[PDB]
Each structure stands twice: as structure tokens, then as C-alpha cells.
Image: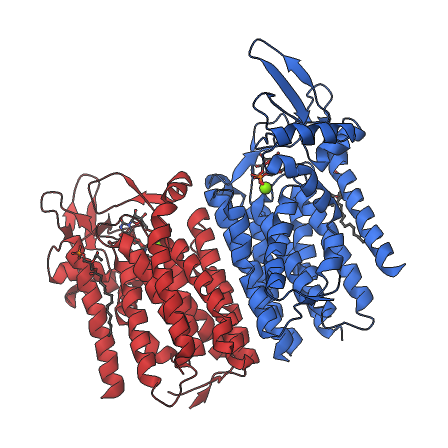
Chain colours: A blue, B red
């Protein structure tokens, strides 16, 4: 039973060591390729290599390619293995192309949909359960759900970002929670689904651990959208093929809140700045809330209602002003990072990430409490 | 029998139209990403977008992802379908990473080996014939051959390059020749191997046709190593899984000659310039042979022997000189493009590519003559 899992653990540890070693080896290449960026929440104007998710993602693929023959050494699970790797690999690829080319916002939705196609087709060919428990047969709409799941998880991680070790950290907690959940369900019942998930979650964990080694505060490298795209698809892939997307989405609680809280800014009903990461008080050294200021006359009818409702619900900190240019509204940037800075006041970057990571652990523990009483 | 082939042809035509439309749409993004280069054989110093093989390659993948359920709508060929796409997709990815990052020469060998792993494992799991006809069982060495085949075809195309429409053009002739060969063998005998090859060769053809639309003289876009990597793996994949790598390698005759003729320069026994593309006589407008000048005292014992042998065989045009700096040897750059310019004299770029393409057609016709008497 654990014979291939042993081999998977062995190659995943080698993959950790590979990721830790290779990340600083390709440093030059990324900086030369202009694949870098400043640490926007630090005074240092130096450029730190970006898109390092491509190196962990690459290690992850090569690990699993070598692993492929072991579970076989029957095709119903083997199809799902090569199928899920196709989807993950295509996603690391289109994700990296997006990092290199900076495609229009439409592709943040089209690329995950594109890459998710092998998962859908494997589910189609291996005769997948289109019926859902609330007892409803969604049919074609179930495949729309599977497509959208990949789109969701990638962007949900990507919009809960911008502080040292958060993106890679939250994924690290999520994969660990999936691993723990798989091991519990490996004791009986649906087992071939959970031994399957472990085959991707063990290598995803140790490679991301190798990435976080160089990403954790102070960040020596940045993960890029390549990592957020990669993570999202790996999670959506194991959720779908393991048939536990419901349970997996509950492990996405901080990501789901942060998304809906961001919805008025994403939909531009309230002006949305390109970067909604907190400000650094250079005197304090700690992070402070970021704000989006705008002319109140330019704001839409629906936008004034949402902002008034969210302020009264003790969620958004709004600040009215009136200069020579006119009357302005300096409202709080709608994200979970800022809401923690609203409630708990200014927080140092290292503790802020670690706080959201703890909040992530809390949610996983709540899900495990829901599911096992 | 042709029901899925009809669907494959339909999506491949849509893929052509997609490639022609999208190539000029992402132009901005590539130039902005510094993914471009000058037309080194033209006076214009403007920068033309590079790595457009990524857009044809991307279209190729999405085409085939949509095609996946059709041959099914049994897993022995379905595994080989998802397996070959994994290898091709990983290769387009690592090929593009190489275009973006400019990795050391070692990776021009490591990336194709890395990406070829799913093919090997599919061949392993689906119980592939390790025995070869000269009757010898190569076993592990057969897998070494499969790995090296991908390495060969990618670089063999990549070193027979540097003139408008050559890289994409030679692949276009090769895929057409594989298509013709498949259709002949579709009449009987081994058929499931040739209907399989057609599934990748039809979409490879029409996407490359869309690429060559913007690449053909005068090049409006450049294909990049991404295309050479992509092409090589798609050809190695169909050759391996179709069991016709021998026949396929004979379609690689101009690529095999150009490789062995380049061997003294590649091995640096004779100095090798980074670009061995012909020179443009600005007065003539036509292309002229390129040369590699070096001090004869610095040349190795083996290098003097090779150069003397190759000169007497009427292959290399050597020119001795002696300035104030010392005695120099200005020998001809060892490539098939230059050998055609040695034998046929200066040739215009458009006719030179078209001449090598004709030479490619000639070789395919020779192979078809070998094989069918
Ligand atoms: C090695 C050196 C290193 O960097 O170690 C750091 C630990 O990293 C984390 O906090 C990273 C946190 C790592 C936690 C990931 C896994 C979390 C939970 C798994 C269990 C979930 C089950 C429910 C400490 O550095 P510091 O700057 O002091 O903070
Ligand atoms: C459309 C407009 C266009 O560009 O068409 C050009 C044709 O392209 C080729 O020559 C490209 C050559 C295309 C040949 C590819 C297929 C070749 C052979 C297939 C059969 C092989 C069987 C053995 C003509 O342009 P020009 O500058 O005059 O040369
Ligand atoms: C709609 C939405 O919510 N978009 C967010 C998303 O955009 P988005 O994903 O587009 O932004 P990027 O992936 O380009 O951001 C990466 C850049 O952010 C900065 N950075 C990133 C990580 C880190 O620990 N420290 C750091 O300073 C660096 O300049 C880095 O180069 O993520 C950004 C931070 O990643 C947030 O500003 C954006 O508001
Ligand atoms: C060992 C070997 O044989 N290496 C060759 C290989 O290197 P290599 O593959 O490394 O070179 P590249 O792929 O970077 O060359 C692409 C560049 O070549 C020029 N270019 C390319 C295509 C074209 O039609 N016109 C044009 O001018 C452009 O500057 C383009 O940007 O291919 C080059 C041309 O592709 C040749 O010079 C090199 O000698
Ligand atoms: Mg991002
Ligand atoms: Mg090249």
C-alpha cells in the first residue's frame, strides 16, 4: 500500500533539496531577463528575482515524471496521473508566459480555463460523476464548475498576496491540510482517490518548502504569478480527481473571504489600485493599511451604497476630505491583509504573514472539526 | 475509421486561423518583454518579435486538448495521447524558459531529456519493444536512444537555421512527409500507430503553417528556440510511439548532414562563432558565405588535420593571411547553408531557404523511394 508512497516521499525530499539549490543558481538569469521586482513594503530599492514558482514548478514536474512508473509497477488511475500532470504543466507554462508577457486581465481567466481542459477530458473519459449532493445531476454545468474551480483557486491565491511568504505559505498550509485529510481517509473507504492526491500533494509540499526557504521574510526571491497559477491548478486537480473539491474549498476559507471582500474593487464599483498591498510607515518599521482615494462625484450609485453598508458593518475605514481640486473619499483597500491591520492596528511584515498563516491553520482545523465532529 | 481524423482536421484548420490571428495580436507583448531580435541578414536594424513558436505551440496544445475526447468517443492509445502531449507541452515550456532566460549550452541537452520522460514511461508502462532490427535487445540502451532522439531532433533543427522561413519550413516538410507516410500505412498493417501520429502531425502542420505565414521572407516574426524544441519533441514523440523513428530519421537527412558537417565547430576543434549564418553583401543584396578566422598557432593538432582533410574533400574554403598581429586562417563556417553558398555561389535569402526546402523535399522523396521501391 505505501510502497509507491515511500518512493514519492523519497523523490519529494530530493525535490526539496533540488529547489533550494537551483533557486539561487538561476538568480542571474531572471535578473538579466528583467524577471524581478522591488520589495514594495521595504525601503530597499533593489530588485529581487521574480517568478521563482517556475523553478519549484519545474522541479515538481521532473520529480513526478520519474515517479510515473512506480504506482503502475490499472490504467484508470494512470490516465488521471498523466492527465493531471498535463493540466498542471500547461498551467505552469501559461502562467510563466503571463509573467513574462503581462497579458491583459482577461487571460487571468482564460489561461486557467485553457489548462484545465485535460482534467475535464480525463473526468469525461474515465466516466466521472456529474451528479452533486446539495441530489442534482448538473451534467454540462458540472464541467463548467470544474473549469471555474481552476480559475478560482489560482486567482484567489494571487489576490491574497504581496507580503513576504504569504502566497507560498498559504499553499503550504493548504497542501499540508490536504495531506493530513488524505492520510485520514487512507485508513479506509475512498482510498484510491486519496493515494492519488498524495502523489501530487507530497511533491507540491516539499518543492514549495524549498521555495519558501528563499521567499520567507526577508524575501530573497519572489514566487510570481507562475506559482499562484501552479498552486491553484494542483489544488483544483487533486480536488476534482479525488472527488473532494467541497472539502478542499473549505480549506480555502481565508482565500474565499478575501475574494468576496475584494469584489467591489475587482468589479471596479469602488476604484481599485493596481497594488492593494499595505503601506510601510518608515518611522515605525511596521505595515499600515493602504487606501484608495477618489472623487465622490465620479463614484457610481451602487458604489456609494456598498461603501456605506461596508462602513456601518465595521469593515471599511472611510475618510472624507475637501481640497482645492474638490471633495475626495479616502476609503480602506478591501483585502484581508488590510482588514487585519484595521482590527489589530499596524503589524510588522513577518508577523503579518505568520498571522494570516495561523488564520489559515485555524480554518483548516475548523474544517477538520466540521468533518469529524 | 476517419471519424476522429475528420474532427482532428477540422480543429487543425481552426488552429491555423487561430495562429495567423494571434501571432500579430501578441506582437506588443513580446517586444515589451524584450523577446525580439534584428534580422541579422538584412540592413534594417529594427527588432522583430521572437519566440513565436510559443503561440503556435500554445494553439497546438489547446487544439489537441479539445480533440482528446474524440478518439475515445481503449486506454492503451489514450495513455499515449495524454503522454505525448505531456512531453510536447513540457518541452514547449522548458523551451520558452530557455528563450526567456538564455540558459547555459548544457540545458540545450538537459531540457529535451527532461521533457522526454513521459514518452519513455508511457513506452515502459504500455510494454514497449526494447528489441531493435539491425535482431538485438537493447533494453536500457533503447531508453537512452529514446531520450537522445528528442535531444537530437530539437538541436538538429535549431542548428539548421538563421534564414527567413527555414526552421519552420523544414518542419513543415518533415510533418507533411510523416502525414503522407502515415496515410500510406493507414491502408493496412500497423494502423493504430499511424492514426496516432496523424493526431499530432495534422495539428503540428497547420499551426506551423500559421507561423510560417508571418515568418516567411520577409520575416515579420521569428520562431525562437521554442519552436525548434517544440518541433523536435513532436517528431521524436510520433516516431517513438508510432514505432517509425528509423523512417522518420531518414526524413531528417539535411538535418543529419548539417549536424555532422558542423561537428568540428560544435566540439570547438575548429573555432565556432556564436552565429554561423551567412553574410549579406549589401552591394549584391544576396547572401554570401560566412567565415571563422583564427590564429593558426592557437589551433589544436586534431583541428589542423580535420581542416586539411575537409579542404581536400572540396567541403571547406580555407584562406591563409598574415598581418602585423600574426598569421591567421580564415576558414568557411561549417554548415549546409554555407556549403550551398560554396557550391552554388551567392544566393538571395528567399531563394536560399526555398532551395534548402526543395533539398528537404528531395530527401523525403529519396526515403519514400527507398521504402516503396
Ligand atoms: C529554516 C529557517 C527559517 O527560515 O525558518 C523560519 C520558519 O518559517 C516559517 O515560519 C514558515 C512556516 C512553516 C509552516 C508550514 C506548515 C504548517 C502547518 C502544517 C500542519 C497543518 C495541519 C492542519 C523561521 O524564521 P523567522 O524569520 O524567525 O520567522
Ligand atoms: C500565402 C502567401 C505566401 O507567402 O506564399 C508564399 C509561398 O510560401 C512558400 O514558399 C512556403 C512553402 C510551403 C511548402 C510546405 C509543404 C511542402 C511540401 C509538402 C509535400 C511533401 C510530400 C513529400 C509565396 O511568397 P514568396 O515571397 O513569393 O515566396
Ligand atoms: C486584484 C488584486 O488583489 N491584485 C493584487 C495582486 O496583483 P498581481 O498578481 O498582478 O501582482 P504581482 O504578482 O505582479 O505582484 C508582485 C510584486 O508585488 C511586490 N511584492 C510581492 C510579494 C512580496 O512579498 N512583496 C512585494 O513587495 C513586488 O513588487 C513583486 O514584484 O497581487 C499584488 C501583490 O502581489 C497586489 O498588490 C494586488 O493588489
Ligand atoms: C551551433 C549553431 O549552429 N548555432 C546556430 C543557432 O544558434 P541559436 O539557436 O542559439 O540562435 P538563436 O535561436 O538565438 O538565433 C535567432 C536570431 O538569429 C537571427 N535570425 C534568425 C532567423 C532568421 O530568419 N533571421 C535572423 O536574422 C535573429 O537575430 C534572431 O533573433 O542558430 C543561429 C541562427 O538562428 C545560428 O547563427 C547559430 O550558428
Ligand atoms: Mg501576483
Ligand atoms: Mg535558435
Q: How many marks?
A: 0
Horizontal side, residue B340 vs residue B300: left or right: left
Q: Residue at x 42, y 58 (%)?
A: B59
User: From where the camera sits, is residue B161 visible?
Assistant: no
Q: Position of residue B34 (x, y in %)?
A: 39, 41
Q: Is residue B100 above or below residue A181?
A: above
Front residue (pair B75, B373): B75
Query: Farthest residue in the right direction?
Result: A373
Q: Is residue B279 above or below residue A236?
A: above
Q: Residue at x 69, y 41 (%)?
A: A260
Horizontal side, residue A137 vs residue B318: left or right: right
- Quarter occupied by the N terminus of chain A: bottom right
Q: Position of residue B287 (x, y in %)?
A: 16, 51
User: From where the camera sits, is residue A372 visible?
Assistant: yes
Horizontal side, residue A167 vs residue A82: left or right: right
Front residue (pair A334, A360): A334
Quarter of the image where one finds residue A282: top right
- Quarter occupied by the C terminus of chain A: bottom right
Locate ligand 1 by image quadrant: top right
Horizontal side, residue A358 vs residue A239: left or right: right
Query: Farthest residue in the top direction?
Result: A324
Q: Is residue B330 above or below residue B200?
A: above
Q: Position of residue A294 (x, y in %)?
A: 59, 22
Q: Residue at x 65, y 64 (%)?
A: A138
Q: Residue at x 68, y 33 (%)?
A: A334
Front residue (pair A163, B335): A163
Q: Position of residue A366 (x, y in %)?
A: 84, 51
Amino acid at each position: 500500500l505505501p510502497m509507491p508512497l515511500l518512493i514519492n516521499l523519497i523523490v519529494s525530499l530530493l525535490g526539496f533539496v533540488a529547489t533550494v539549490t537551483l533557486i539561487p543558481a538561476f538568480r542571474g538569469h531572471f535578473i538579466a531577463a528583467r524577471l524581478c521586482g522591488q520589495d514594495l513594503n521595504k525601503t530597499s530599492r533593489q530588485q529581487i528575482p521574480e517568478s521563482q514558482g517556475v523553478i519549484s514548478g519545474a522541479v515538481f514536474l521532473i520529480i513526478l515524471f520519474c515517479f510515473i512508473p512506480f504506482p503502475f509497477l490499472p490504467h484508470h488511475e494512470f490516465v488521471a496521473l498523466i492527465g493531471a500532470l498535463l493540466a498542471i504543466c500547461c498551467m505552469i507554462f501559461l502562467g510563466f508566459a503571463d509573467d513574462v508577457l503581462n497579458l491583459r486581465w482577461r487571460h487571468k481567466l482564460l489561461l486557467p480555463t485553457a489548462a484545465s481542459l485535460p482534467l475535464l477530458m480525463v473526468y469525461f473519459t474515465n466516466f466521472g460523476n456529474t451528479t452533486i449532493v446539495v441530489h442534482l445531476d448538473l451534467g454540462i454545468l458540472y464541467y463548467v464548475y470544474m473549469g471555474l474551480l481552476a480559475v478560482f483557486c489560482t486567482n484567489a491565491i494571487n489576490i491574497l498576496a504581496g507580503i513576504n511568504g504569504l502566497e507560498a505559505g498559504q499553499s503550504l498550509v493548504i497542501s499540508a491540510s490536504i495531506i493530513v485529510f488524505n492520510l485520514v481517509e487512507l485508513e479506509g473507504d475512498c482510498r484510491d482517490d486519496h493515494v492519488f492526491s498524495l502523489y501530487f500533494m507530497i511533491p507540491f509540499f516539499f518543492t514549495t518548502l524549498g521555495l519558501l526557504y528563499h521567499n520567507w521574510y526577508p524575501s530573497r526571491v519572489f514566487v510570481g504569478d507562475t506559482f499562484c497559477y501552479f498552486a491553484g491548478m494542483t489544488f483544483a486537480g487533486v480536488g476534482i480527481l479525488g472527488h473532494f473539491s467541497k472539502t478542499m474549498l473549505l480549506f480555502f476559507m481565508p482565500q474565499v473571504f478575501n475574494f468576496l471582500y475584494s469584489l467591489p474593487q475587482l468589479l471596479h464599483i469602488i476604484p481599485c489600485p493596481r497594488h492593494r498591498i499595505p503601506r510601510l510607515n518608515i518611522k515605525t518599521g511596521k505595515l499600515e493599511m493602504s487606501y484608495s482615494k477618489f472623487k465622490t462625484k465620479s463614484l457610481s450609485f451602487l458604489g456609494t451604497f456598498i461603501l456605506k453598508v461596508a462602513e456601518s458593518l465595521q469593515l471599511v475605514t472611510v475618510h472624507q476630505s475637501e481640497t482645492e481640486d474638490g471633495e475626495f473619499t479616502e476609503c480602506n483597500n478591501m483585502t484581508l491583509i488590510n482588514l487585519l491591520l484595521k482590527v489589530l492596528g499596524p503589524i510588522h511584515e513577518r508577523n503579518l504573514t505568520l498571522l494570516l498563516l495561523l488564520l489559515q491553520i485555524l480554518g483548516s482545523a475548523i474544517t477538520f472539526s466540521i468533518r469529524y465532529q
